[PDB]
Image (cartoon, rainbow, N blue to C red; front, side, top):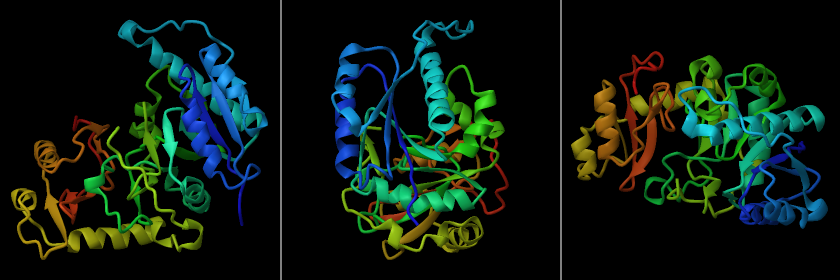
Length: 331
């Protein structure tokens, strides 16, 4: 069954929200199934005029409080981040309380969507509703540069412990949990903390369904995949944690230097094992994978495993299988 899922576009003072809206409107399959609500903060007149010119194709709402926010002593340079957090709190409150929608896909104004962006969320929304171990579906692959993704598998999806944002679906139920403790600033890194995440994962793709414009190297998928016609049961936690983990640890192990230099090419899928924070950093860097960690979680990591393509080979940068939780001190 098809479900109504609003798209909440977060805008402020960039006239290029035009490019974001033009792509969303071009690919939208139904205005009824995907109403677009553009929440504009900042009161930038030119941007307001641009949004208004779309007329009824979107609903334009305006964050009401344009005042400066009192910041804490360590944050004089970060007024903008306090304003962003205030805008998200207000806009999500509008989509879930005033409009009373059951879920929403949050899209920053500098994101261009892929042709199957809507199909992807329509197909994954039922997974999010049914699996309490998931808390979001994201269009973003943090290691999604062209040379690091398999273009022959545009349909492949994964679970990740690293909340990616950048085009993401959440349920009204999650907003009910987050709203009472919403932070003053740095909302996305706050969601990445264990006190918020509570061990929950997001679905993310092999090839990103959003790309930033105006991170710049992430490749936007251009081959339409009919996700609603595919069997996505493999993403259920019980199946995924058995099958994907058996796949990762069943793969032959190779030293990082051998992967880097393309040795043993007959092995199309391998595992590079790291044992501590220093080796994770070093190995990630050697293979061109993002090496920063938020609350101890690596970008696109799942049970500590970062999966990507390297010189055409599938690689799993993984901890020993005795892994049992993230350590926030891995900074």
